[PDB]
Amino acid sequence: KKKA
Amino acid sequence: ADVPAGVQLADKQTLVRNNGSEVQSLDPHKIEGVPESNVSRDLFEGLLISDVEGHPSPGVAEKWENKDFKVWTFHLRENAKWSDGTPVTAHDFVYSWQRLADPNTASPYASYLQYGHIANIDDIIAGKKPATDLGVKALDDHTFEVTLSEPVPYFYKLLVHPSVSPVPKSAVEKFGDKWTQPANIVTNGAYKLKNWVVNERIVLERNPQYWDNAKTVINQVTYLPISSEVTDVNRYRSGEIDMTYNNMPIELFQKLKKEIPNEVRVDPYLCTYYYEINNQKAPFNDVRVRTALKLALDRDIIVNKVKNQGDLPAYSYTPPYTDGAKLVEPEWFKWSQQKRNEEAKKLLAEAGFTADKPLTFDLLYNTSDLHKKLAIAVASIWKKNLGVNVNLENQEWKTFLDTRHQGTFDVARAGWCADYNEPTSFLNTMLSDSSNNTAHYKSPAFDKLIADTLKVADDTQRSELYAKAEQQLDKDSAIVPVYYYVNARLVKPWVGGYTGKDPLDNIYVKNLYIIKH
Ligand code: IUM
Ligand code: IUM
Ligand code: IUM
Ligand code: IUM
Ligand code: IUM
């Protein structure tokens, strides 16, 4: 998942 | 939640969490980030969930079996229900996984069914066969059967991810894109959506139909969208936020460690921070240009003298502590910075980038104090060690994701966290056709290395193939690795149930509880  | 004997519980069981930014969506087939997944785990539950230490455990499926790692059968619990009282059945999963695979859904995680190798996924993704052809079947209302095209021993580890959670067909089909509004949404997790105010808050309340509802303690949880780490800290310490987002401000960190050391939680995290290069955009399509950026970046200054929050300088994409990773350290990582700079200057000069004609490009990051401070320090190191001109640009989260998928960027701040603890959770995102490939990296040599891992039935050759795949990415300089994260955040002393033991940080608010204070 892309981590903000 | 499993409350210890002797703990006194507060009278009001409510929790406020900061979530980093406004989510891209509440539909599980349309999300790709950590903010999106934090809220999704509390609303939608899939076959397995993670326990408080991170291990894959029973969710909707009570038990499951496999035949040769190729045919997996899940026995769904009879009391699993949606928030409207209707039962969660195997048919919900057939519908949901075909909707995820369907090109029309345009899910950023379409490829997650490829990672799992469900029969026929490649043809469905390519428009060659209808989604109804997917290798999943409901043998009855309580038995879901999945067929893979190859043996995948770690298959069930993937199932804790939001993309493979169920969606309620009746709401999706009646409201389209507004099926997620509070008045229309139907959920099967421990909470249901109460309120959603864009750029203000998301409020969830307990879902009484949840099968494990008798163990849920918190009745209400609010998710805030604050992307300023300094503001998240201020509001935490003034008493409004019980748990920060896990981005810590360079401005206050050392001081919090000194002042409220018991509240500062720092644990291992399987995520890598890096600068994503658009591999298809000139002049970034030249390996010398990418290698110079990778080498001229001084990780010791950035990690240890600028951020200084416990991260480890990185030399690869997959974190070296991932289960099954046996990576070899590249020799450039072993050199001095001085030698890296000289080599970098040399390669940039070979590409046609003089002092008379510096390379100039944009560095895009998602609005944030932390990413801005890091981008400023990096633009500065690249200027000093290479003579390149860097234009900093910030974008709100959901737009920033969009820009990267579209390819309208040069270089972008990035960070990938594992979805399951196995090296393909990282490596599959660099496949040429992966829907998560925002590097726009296309390498047939890399793709073949990953394909072969499932053709061997030996974990030593699989690991050896993962280490060669990291070496291929390194050779191509597909990205600029910066650091391997530590998960750092503040948690009030009265928030019980958070161990910090799961390296994937799969928190469920249903496992937490507020101690009387
Ligand atoms: O499933 U085994 O090495
Ligand atoms: O349970 U095993 O490789
Ligand atoms: O814990 U194991 O492969
Ligand atoms: O430097 U420009 O897109
Ligand atoms: O808080 U300030 O860049």
Image (cartoon, rainbow, N blue to C red):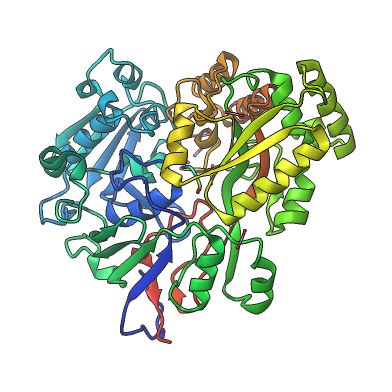
Residue B142 appears anywhere in the view? yes
Residue B135 appears anywhere in the view? no
Q: How many marks?
A: 0
Q: Position of residue B135 (x, y in %)?
A: 27, 25
Residue beneath the point at 16% across and 53% down: B82
> In the drawing, does residue B484 fall left or right of residue B245?
right
Residue beneath the point at 33% across and 21% down: B125
**Quarter of the rendered image showing ligand 4:** top right
Q: Nearer the viewer, residue B104 or B460?
A: B104
Q: Nearer the viewer, residue B452 or B235?
A: B235
If the image is split into quadrants, where does the N terminus of chain B sit?
Answer: bottom left
Q: Position of residue B517 (x, y in %)?
A: 43, 87
Residue beneath the point at 65% across and 30% down: B361
Q: Residue furthest front?
A: B356
* B513 up-or-down from B456: above or below: below
* B376 up-or-down from B423: above or below: below
